[PDB]
Image (cartoon, rainbow over all chains, first blue to last red; front, side):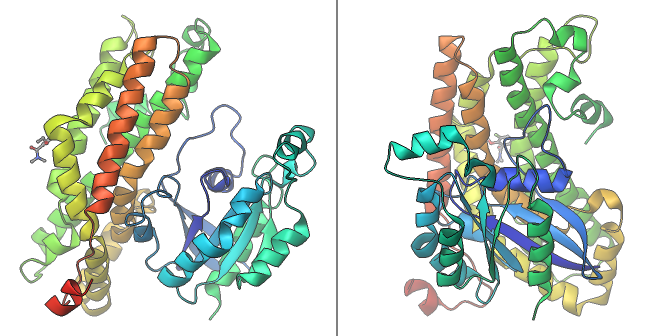
Length: 179
Length: 245
Ligand SMILES: CCOc1c(F)cccc1C(=O)N(C)C
């Protein structure tokens, strides 16, 4: 197995920590959802290739511009997350997160991931967003942002139901393996 | 870690660590508060274990087996003794607060009601000045340690054999040298997340809510000072590159 490093970035409300927890346990915790994620090394076999994929979160580093870049050395793939229940988290992708990752991780593939996709059709979410003249992020809005920022691709998932989570990490492994 | 503490923190939560007959005696809000305090202590136990792998397995094994040039082991593991002393002392205080709270006849059933004062003490006065000095130094030497490790692993056969030997066991899967360095750098920014969630479930006693609010502010003051005090050191950087920052 070859060793690769993945880092997830995005705003504090994007669901990055929950995504790493659900993937690393293959389960949405039934008793207690952890507040933080330390690290994990996943054994993944994608398209016949075995990889040890080390996983890292940047949660807690969003306000600290000199500490946060210490998470980036030798990253092989970036997951850049936003929450589908937060058009504000998607607005911060192109001119805050993208220029930072392009600077510290040149030529590293970025996968833009829309988290919490289960909230797109949640009535409570639609009511709260309508008070700020907003609506859940549409799939075309996510794909267009991924296209504009030069992402390797666009994916969606729900940490709550686990739908799409395995696929995001198998594709991140393929992106990390590419020349 | 020692077996007594590993077993005390083996469960995924406080609600799974305590006896079910003891859990049943508490309100849901108390269970939510205790589950987050248990995560703060469990992750602190693991952080001190990361620092023991750095000092005992890596640093001391390199001094006792390899013929590295002087200053190289300190370059790989900057400030590790000072970091171990800070966190082993803090972990000792957290574990003593739990032990004092145990019910007679039990080694597992407890409730910690007064965490805020312990966090104010850790994150104020001389211990906070020491944490600020040590993390400003460690985090400024983080890139240099990673580069020194990669250079030695690629060029020195005995170093490569030593690393592959001591990191082979499955219990070291998440704890290679570079992984330990980044686990330590990231520890300090986990504290606000944990304290804020403990505070969310600590409104029942107003003195506790106030003390956790004071501790949260002190931790963010420490993080702001560390972040402003970092400048990455680089082997071979010339004075002109530095004064033209
Ligand atoms: C000044 C207090 O800092 C410490 C601490 F909080 C625990 C253990 C040791 C130390 C210490 O004196 N240094 C030099 C790190």
